[PDB]
Amino acid sequence: MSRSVLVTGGNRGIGLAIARAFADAGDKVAITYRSGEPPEGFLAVKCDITDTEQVEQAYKEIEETHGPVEVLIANAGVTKDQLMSEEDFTSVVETNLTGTFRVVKRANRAMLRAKKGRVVLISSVVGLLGSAGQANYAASKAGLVGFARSLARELGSRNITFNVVAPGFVDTQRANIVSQVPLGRYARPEEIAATVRFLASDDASYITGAVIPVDGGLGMG
Amino acid sequence: MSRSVLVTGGNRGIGLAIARAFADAGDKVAITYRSGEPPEGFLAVKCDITDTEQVEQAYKEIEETHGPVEVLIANAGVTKDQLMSEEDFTSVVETNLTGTFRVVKRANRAMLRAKKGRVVLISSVVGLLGSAGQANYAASKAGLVGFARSLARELGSRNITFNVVAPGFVDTQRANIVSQVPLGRYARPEEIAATVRFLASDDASYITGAVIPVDGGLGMG
Amino acid sequence: MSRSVLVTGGNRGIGLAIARAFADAGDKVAITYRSGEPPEGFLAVKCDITDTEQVEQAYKEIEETHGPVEVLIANAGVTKDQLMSEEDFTSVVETNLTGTFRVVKRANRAMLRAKKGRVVLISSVVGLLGSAGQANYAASKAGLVGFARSLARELGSRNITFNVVAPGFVDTQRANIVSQVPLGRYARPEEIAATVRFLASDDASYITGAVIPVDGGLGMG
Amino acid sequence: MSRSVLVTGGNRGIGLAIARAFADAGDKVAITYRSGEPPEGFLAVKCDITDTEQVEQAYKEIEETHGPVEVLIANAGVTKDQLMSEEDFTSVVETNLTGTFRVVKRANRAMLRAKKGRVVLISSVVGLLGSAGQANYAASKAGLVGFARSLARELGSRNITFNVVAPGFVDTQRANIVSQVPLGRYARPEEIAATVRFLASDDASYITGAVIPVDGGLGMG
């Protein structure tokens, strides 16, 4: 019943809402974080996920406590500490992709052996951004989608799915921001978590290489 | 608790599977169908949804019994009976869009008054097609996606969502057809239904203008 | 030096502008047209390109005079005379695709034998449209793009390219229509023609399956 | 007649083919490079384009010799020196975006004053890549496209266009590589340069925010 779930970047914001939703549903939830005191209720591993050896030890620790990760949620969104000019910020965007590659590659090893797995990558929450900021956003998301689709092709018929959830504006002047959202409101973080939970369930077993926008119509056209 | 649900094209295949999933979930489910026999257990109206008068009469009958439609599932996929050269088949593509336009426009009246609604459009199951075949498939699916996105923008902030579920290959020589599907198998119709049920749920309230492929990674790249 | 060029729908507007650009460049240019008067200076065949026999006869006549068609420009855009409710207009969308399928399939015979060809499909000029209107537009354009890509894959390495030019707003109240165009003006028809001429040139030999928007940034995002 | 053109990364490969094509056409061509002896025929400025102050001086030097840049070609493709594991390589991908932002922002200042300009961004040549490599590729391209589209919207009706050229495989085992290319061959670098020249010409004045794939059908679907 209860699964071993890992949410990287699950200490705050949408990452935390996702982590809580899995724990509230009865899964065994671990998270990674860089700094601060982590939220209550989780196996929390302080580490830099850009570092192969730190990721190895994180997974060691998680596998020894919860068993091998069956569901990986890689929250690749821009964190607090990170969010500098937009131009220099692309270096932060690159560090988020690199960490994602490493945690996913490490999780795939055990999922391959189990002949079952769920990998869900979460792009950054949308904010108001200049041209270079919008480029960095587009690059970050396409990187996730490109990675997910490649892994789906590479892994083939091993019952491991790879999907991306793309949040829009999320509630964490308000009228001026929502004026570009057809639904005319901010998302609640729980709305993002519900989609993540759906993709991680047996009901989504035939969905792979997909990007699911949870954005109120914002980016549809 | 139970909602008034309408599935157009709901007497067989994916449409029937969708109707059953909402019935199992405790909703009041009506279907329309063009030909054949109705499934047992459902309020069923035989009609040609390309005819505005027949559409109004089907809705009148259904809603007298179940109340105004709160969830509309327009199964626009090519039907058994339709399944001609491709050049002539463009007329069937035309009529499939026409029918979808008529049933959705009718449903939007009550949904707008209720300030809530769910409209999910289902594209055709994928087949092996030549060039004009693939063109007609691309035209049919894009018509649905364009319709859903335009409606999302037009209805704006009235809590009515419009989404498209795009099935891949669905089980309704086999190993040769599914050699192009990364997950290496056909979808069960119930898998399509599970996604439709999720989109119709309150958990998917912020998803609109979206196309969700349930295709095992077939059309991703 | 001079090639045999055919522009279907080439008696007015963008189609005429395209025919003139190839004529100015020194090509032997034929056109087909459904109704109206033919432009002076061109081999012109009055015919209904949805009728296989009429298409064969138009090509027979044209090629006797100019030699086998080496460049086909299929102007599939909604015509003056076509320009109905949107529900009925889906039949015009159907016939516009049908005509395009017939003229291209006919051209491919000689191009395959020659091991060289250029096929450029032109989508409809953009207008202000409601929901089903936008759907029909999206369906028409996607049909062309799907056709071109399928043909590129099917013909493979025979040096025949298939591309789509997608005009935005074209000059054939004004300030209100072009307030959504980032460049802030209408296209001149000659601007559409210049892109078509480039795609037909030997300089565009490696471009195939592409959709090139000439739209002032209108449909980009 | 003769324009001031700058090709960043124009010292080798496709960048050099583009630079030569503009110089052969009679334009005044400057290039930036990091190391090595630059090719003959160009005003060549050794600099790190990730550095705002080095970019400022580069442009100073170019503007004093050739006059303000009227055409900027930003070759954001992965260079020699750069092309490490795919995972660590995303840092290189981020440095390429940052340099692009800076050179474009600097060129926009003079183009805005001239009320005319051409900005063309060139994505990486395609190679055979693992999952993390394909993600890095997708991120790099989407970053360029996202930047171009944002600038097109931001600049509005100032007659400055922003476009992306996406090369496929370019000629700089061969049968196994080309087996995924519909046209069944590598591009010649001159084919990429010809498209760049077209976008930079007055004939492409209504094309902006567009991505033009020069890939033989490779990435069309």
Image (spheres, coloured by chain):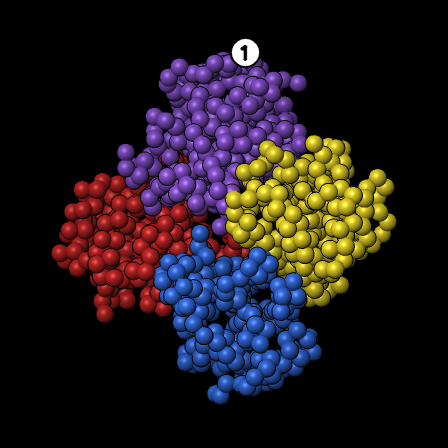
Chain colours: A purple, B yellow, C blue, D red
The answer to whether residue C45 is visible is yes
- Give me the residue at 31% from left, 62% from top: D159
Where is residue B212 shown, x and y percent of the image? 60, 42
Image position of D143 with respect to B105: above or below: above
- Give me the residue at 50% from left, 31% from top: A188
Q: Is residue D56 left or right of residue A20?
A: left
- Give me the residue at 15% from left, 52% from top: D61
Image position of C120 with respect to D119: above or below: below
The residue beneath circle 1 is A65
Where is residue D163 shown, x and y percent of the image? 37, 56
Give the farthest residue toward the bottom.
Answer: C40
Identified by mark 1, the residue type is Thr
Host chain of mark 1: A
SS label for mark 1 = helix
Quarter of the image for the N terminus of chain A: give it: top right
Image position of C105 with respect to A18: above or below: below
